[PDB]
Image: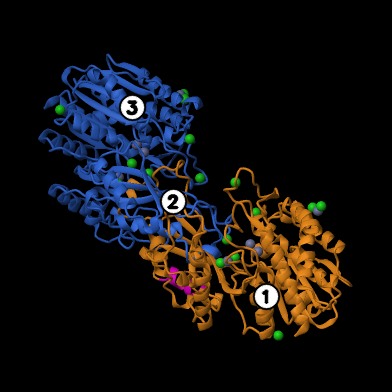
Chain colours: A orange, B blue
Amino acid sequence: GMFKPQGLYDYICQQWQEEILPSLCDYIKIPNKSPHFDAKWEEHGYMEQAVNHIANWCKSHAPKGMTLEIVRLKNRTPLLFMEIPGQIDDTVLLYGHLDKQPEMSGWSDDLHPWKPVLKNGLLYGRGGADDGYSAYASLTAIRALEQQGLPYPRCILIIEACEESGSYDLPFYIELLKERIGKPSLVICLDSGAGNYEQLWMTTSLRGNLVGKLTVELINEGVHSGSASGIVADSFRVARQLISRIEDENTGEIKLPQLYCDIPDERIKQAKQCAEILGEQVYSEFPWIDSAKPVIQDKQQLILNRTWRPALTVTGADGFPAIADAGNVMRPVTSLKLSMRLPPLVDPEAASVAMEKALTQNPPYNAKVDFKIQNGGSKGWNAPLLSDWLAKAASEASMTYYDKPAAYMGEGGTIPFMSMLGEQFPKAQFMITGVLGPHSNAHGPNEFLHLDMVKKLTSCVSYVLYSFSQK
Amino acid sequence: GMFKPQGLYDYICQQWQEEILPSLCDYIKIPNKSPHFDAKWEEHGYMEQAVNHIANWCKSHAPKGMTLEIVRLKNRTPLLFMEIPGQIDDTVLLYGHLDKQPEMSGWSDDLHPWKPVLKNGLLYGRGGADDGYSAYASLTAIRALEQQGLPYPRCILIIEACEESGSYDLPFYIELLKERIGKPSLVICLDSGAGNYEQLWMTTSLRGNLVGKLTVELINEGVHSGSASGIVADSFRVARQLISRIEDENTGEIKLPQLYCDIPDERIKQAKQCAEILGEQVYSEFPWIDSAKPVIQDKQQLILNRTWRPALTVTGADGFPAIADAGNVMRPVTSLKLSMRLPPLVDPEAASVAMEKALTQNPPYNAKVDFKIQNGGSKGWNAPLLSDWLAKAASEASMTYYDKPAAYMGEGGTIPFMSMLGEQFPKAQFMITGVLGPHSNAHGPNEFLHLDMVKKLTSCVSYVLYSFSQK
Ligand SMILES: [Cl-]
Ligand SMILES: [Cl-]
Ligand SMILES: [Cl-]
Ligand SMILES: [Cl-]
Ligand SMILES: [Cl-]
Ligand SMILES: [Cl-]
Ligand SMILES: [Cl-]
Ligand SMILES: [Cl-]
Ligand SMILES: [Cl-]
Ligand SMILES: [Cl-]
Ligand SMILES: [Cl-]
Ligand SMILES: [Cl-]
Ligand SMILES: [Cl-]
Ligand SMILES: [Cl-]
Ligand SMILES: [Cl-]
Ligand SMILES: [Cl-]
Ligand SMILES: [Zn+2]
Ligand SMILES: [Zn+2]
Ligand SMILES: [Zn+2]
Ligand SMILES: [Zn+2]
Ligand SMILES: [Zn+2]
Ligand SMILES: [Zn+2]
Ligand SMILES: [Zn+2]
Ligand SMILES: [Zn+2]
């Protein structure tokens, strides 16, 4: 009778076109890099511009009874908080972020990180997809239920401004806000990936991440390499030898058992199913150069590599002159930034201790070796047992708006707040989902928000909120 | 009777103190970086200042009949040429350079690369020892024989300005000057090392050197590492795997047989003797950090590692953000500058082909891999059979001025012109020697010229020139 699922989609599409898109485009212009990428973010004022821009829009599109506050702690990024009272005596917590990754290199000639460009049904620019859409879609999902005169639960929306720097500000806000937030029964987060743009993707796990700096030195100044080569070990050779203690150079297999966990059987089964759904799109849509290929061909194992196994990337370095600048001097120091994704269930403290010991003990040639972990190292997340009402709601929503079943897969990235919530609220259910499908390029050049996908996804969120109301 | 060996030393010491040192100190102020370190060297005018400074001094300290010319080819570094006719119908060719390595980091607070500082009998500054002293000492060695009224051979002095960039200009000058230079019977080069500051060191070999850029890419833009890690091999892992094809990470042993030669037995014997002379000073005087140690403890083998075996150093890199700047993005490209010293007898072309094939064939994961060698890759040198007259002259000179025997050892660095001369003039004898002993720090911070050493060395050169006259 009161609930019209296609009415939800029609309203949500109109809202996306007429109300959201202009505002979101204006948000893309704001160069509000997260604090790790701009230590002077406060002085520069862009973060403040962004939170006021999104807050302004929320206030003019407010559900009934909404309290909105830009919450502020000293020297911290601001936090956008909304409380929508609803009529049902239960709470849902919706989360996203509004801070951005930096420009990056490789933008197409017609595209720019701080210039919104709408082409081929895609909205290009930094932060449209990751994660500017989140506040808009979350609030619109509630507004769509009000359009139909339907009741809904109490909703708390948290749109933070430190996520791209590890959410280090967030625990302080949650301590301030704890009693006001209360106990959510459902957590919705619109900052995750999608296997394709054809169905609803439910994230069943997130990896942890630990970042540190490995420094290796044998000598305290640069030395003529003719004199030294053959007697003084080069610090680069010692550094790569140390990395071989933790990672096999041929396969990439991490050698430290403390960086693995047992993978739940249901996640192995889900990976099999997702391999069948995606086929070669498990890997084919990475920006491979020439005939480059993935580390192995088995699609299920690739999914598990990405979701349930540790993996190292070397993301920066100090101590190297530019090649065109360089003479032949043997360098005094090699420093490498090591970024280690962790399986969902691995404790970052235990993994940190294991990495530091493996990399620093018994130094080759009594080299001076340090491995300094960055604070803000964060645990992954594994979904709790899925409630029947949410399995049904997700399936129904996906079939309604995509005409395809909901699909369940792990996410290879890291969203620190989900681990926090899963620990604080062990009985909460989660809907962690998003729009970051193939070529969406979060953290990369030519980032886009897929508009068809986000309209359908916003509808799914609204449908699940309605379903929550009925359980 | 006419020859007074101590008279040579007395005059040479007075000349060093009164005539050379002020001029050499003024030369240290000139920041004439070699072209590899300053592409605008011609515009900047420092190279021209340096060659005119040394030429001015030579003209005012000229032996009889000297022709001096600053020889110039279009767009090439200038070349300082002297011809001193002498009275004996044979030719000696004396060589050094006046171009400089750049500043480097790590200078002591009271010291500066372009500020001469004389302390503790040492002259600090860039280019005093490597290799500004060479023109002064070479000309003074001849002047000392004129002081005594002694005859000497025809002498050609070549002081080039491209040595620190691989002497790429020099073949063009030698083609221009070939017929004027004629056929030297003895080559003296004052740009080599010394095991200690206590005796004459005769260089019996020089290593070759090949430099190239290794580039590895799997993807054509940076990608979110959460998405990619576990599926797309990191380019750093592939690069270190490739380096393991050519170098064992545990020992530093080069794995390519084409980069080794047979070591002449007499050089193995000489290394044994030099190990006995030097003891732990084979390695103890490198600037080790904390308790860092050399790659092995065997002193003779360390000498041979440094002189007769290939060795790799990684001297620069492109494609890495600074660690404090960096996010966690998987990088599109890893590029490393590889500097490979070669044994004296190894052909750099054959070694180049072997390195490029080993590094680029069968690329892991069909990565895009390139290894591009820098032109100006240069062969080492091995001394010819030592003539009895020169063995005697070197021994006599060393005993006279140092009260210790001459010592014979290989040099781990590279002087391209010596290979050129050894090929062009197979019957020439060589006296390749110098002042670069422990802590002298050529190519490093706090470079110094040891003044006692250089006075005695200049005397040895003069003694050997007198001996040449008598054979
Ligand atoms: Cl910054
Ligand atoms: Cl704005
Ligand atoms: Cl605005
Ligand atoms: Cl760009
Ligand atoms: Cl060097
Ligand atoms: Cl050496
Ligand atoms: Cl992430
Ligand atoms: Cl709970
Ligand atoms: Cl330059
Ligand atoms: Cl001058
Ligand atoms: Cl002057
Ligand atoms: Cl310095
Ligand atoms: Cl990333
Ligand atoms: Cl992923
Ligand atoms: Cl060299
Ligand atoms: Cl000859
Ligand atoms: Zn605005
Ligand atoms: Zn995000
Ligand atoms: Zn992000
Ligand atoms: Zn993903
Ligand atoms: Zn001058
Ligand atoms: Zn030199
Ligand atoms: Zn040099
Ligand atoms: Zn040496």
What amino acid does circle 3 point to?
Ile
What range is drawn magenta here? A352-361
| Residue B145 painted magenta | no
Residue at which label 1 appears: A431
Q: Is residue A264 above or below residue B329?
A: below
Task: Give the side of residue B390 with respect to residue B128, left or right.
Answer: left
Give the number of the disc on residue B159.
Answer: 3
Residue A206 visible somewhere in the drawing: no
Residue B56, percent from left and from top: 40, 20
On screen, residue B424 versus residue B228, left or right, reads left
Q: CA distance from mark 3 to mark 1?
A: 76 Å
Labels 2, 3: one chain: no
> Which sits in the foreground, A138 or B364?
A138
Looking at the image, residue B34 sits to the left or right of residue B247; the answer is right
Residue at (39% x, 25% y) in the render: B76
Whole-percent x, y for residue A360 in the image: 44, 69
Number of other residues with Cα within 10 Å of mark 2, as a class: few under 14, some 14 to 19, many 20 or more: few
Q: Quadrant of ligand 16?
A: top left
